[PDB]
Image: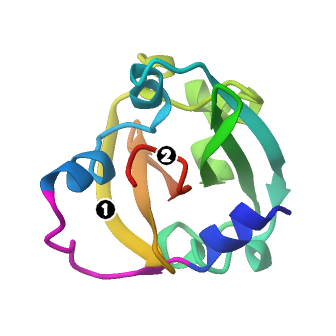
Amino acid sequence: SHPALTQLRALRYSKEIPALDPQLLDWLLLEDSMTKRFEQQGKTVSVTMIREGFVEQNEIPEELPLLPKESRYWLREILLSADGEPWLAARTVVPVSTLSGPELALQKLGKTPLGRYLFTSSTLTRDFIEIGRDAGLWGRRSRLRLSGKPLLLTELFLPASPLY
């Protein structure tokens, strides 16, 4: 567990995207994880692994309504740091049926940070994104498809990040 992941789990989402200033929407609707955009700020990015493993439905109560109902899921919870400073917390939930073919590598990522630069083989698409907030902080959750196979990605932007 970790205090940033506990705050991530409390985000409250709105069905409709709020009319935020453009600079902030540009960051939140980005069509990729934040890895390369944070590197773009002139920073080295590293992952701190908070939890990785197969879990059952009882452990993903918030993501379950957006994904197929299956017996098991791959859960990945990390902290991403820019030059040693935490900038973001993220939680990814993958139905085990998405872990087939090339997508099985999502399982062995470890501390490599997620990003489109790594999945040049599959067709990547997003069929849903919502923005959320909890006490001054922004976050978002999306349903991405690799080769048509779904996964849920939730990100929380910590106050030290460039969105604030």
Q: Residue at label 2?
A: 161
Residue name at image x 82 percent, y 49 percent: 50
Asked if 145 appears above or below 139 in the picture, the reply is above
Q: Could you tell me the amino acid type at mark 1? A: Phe
> 145 or 34, which lies in front?
34
| Helix, strand or loop for the magenta stretch, by majority | loop
Q: Which residues are magenta?
A: 11-21
Instruction: Kindly report the distance in space between the C-alpha atoms of the residues bearing marks 2 and 1.
Output: 24 Å
The C terminus is located in which quarter? bottom left
Magenta run includes residue 15: yes
Q: Reading the chain from its start, which is encountered first: label 2 or label 1?
A: 1
Residue name at image x 78 percent, y 79 percent: 58
Residue name at image x 53 percent, y 56 percent: 159
Closer mark to the observer between disc 2 and disc 1: 2
> 151 or 23, which lies in front?
23
Residue 76 horizontal side relative to residue 24, left or right: right
Residue name at image x 15 percent, y 61 percent: 21
Q: How is the image coloured?
A: rainbow
Q: Position of residue 157 (x, y in %)?
A: 50, 55
Residue contact at pointers 2 and 1, CB within 8 angstroms: no
Name the image quarter holding residue 142.
bottom left
Residue 102 horizontal side relative to residue 49, left or right: left
Q: Position of residue 66 (x, y in %)?
A: 47, 71
Q: Position of residue 84 (x, y in %)?
A: 71, 30
Magenta run includes residue 138: no
Local crowd size for mark 1, using a 10 Å CA cut-off: few (<14), some (14–19), many (≥20): few
- Count of numbered badges drawn on the protein: 2
Q: Secondary structure at mark 2?
A: loop
Q: Could you tell me the amino acid type at mark 2? A: Ser
Residue 51 horizontal side relative to residue 84, left or right: right
Q: Using the image, tell me which numbered label, if any, was put on residue 128.
A: 1
> 54 or 147, which lies in front?
54
